[PDB]
Image 1 (spheres, rainbow, N blue to C red):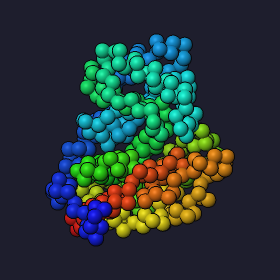
Image 2: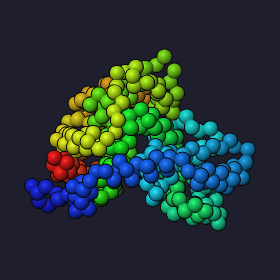
Image 3: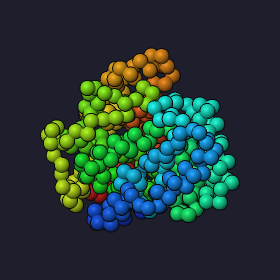
Image 4: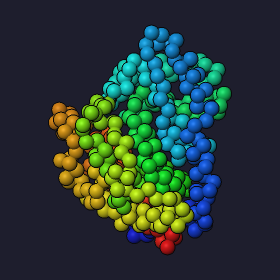
Length: 348
């Protein structure tokens, strides 16, 4: 792409076949699967085996495991990983900008337990990452597990569940766009979670979802460091938000405008902002628009402000200092815009 920037990157054929093909597969086959995978017996086995394995290593330390990720929110497939947050020592409400020594120390002790155990196969141990994780395979079930010591993923999974349950069209669209991302081979640049926040933002602009900020009007906040992770589970009827019945004409119509919107989106001056949920949130004005806990945190820690000087800015609505698409390149962004344009055309 870097060469021949004047040429629209051709939509990969695998993606073209799916877009031009009936959109009914999501409505009829992939959705029932995603809904079933929110809960299955295998999840209980994994948690119980994880506790049995880790409780001896930290014997009098309190320990709780949390499920989260695509499987739990209802947009997963049978090959999806299972994300797990292991909380040792009631560290749920502690935010670490960078993984502390204790966090890396815990993860190394856990690395050893997985290697020694016959029920687990250690896959990847990553310690030089914003969120260090352990990747293992639970051999009894075959499910690959992503284990972290950070609660933020669990908190936004709870938010997504409320969004999907309140407005199922959101869930249908995320499944479609998740599959679109894989067939476009863009998963390394743009995560499933990033595209979920983009769908939520787009629906907010269609007055079908509330701004996350409007769900956090302090009456009392629950905090992970400086971040407000709880939200008011307001009925949509109270906010005048219509709950649409997801049908194939609906979904296709909103998907067309979704791809159209982000094909013409001005990524140089604006950011995807589900926190504010308003149109045309300027990169220049966003930091003034955040809540007081953010302003206090960056004032004390300026190096922890959101990374706005990147080609693509998608702000996490809870961890307000995190740009989920900070690693996207100019050519990764162009590729995504080109695919969006060609995808919008194929939906009429």
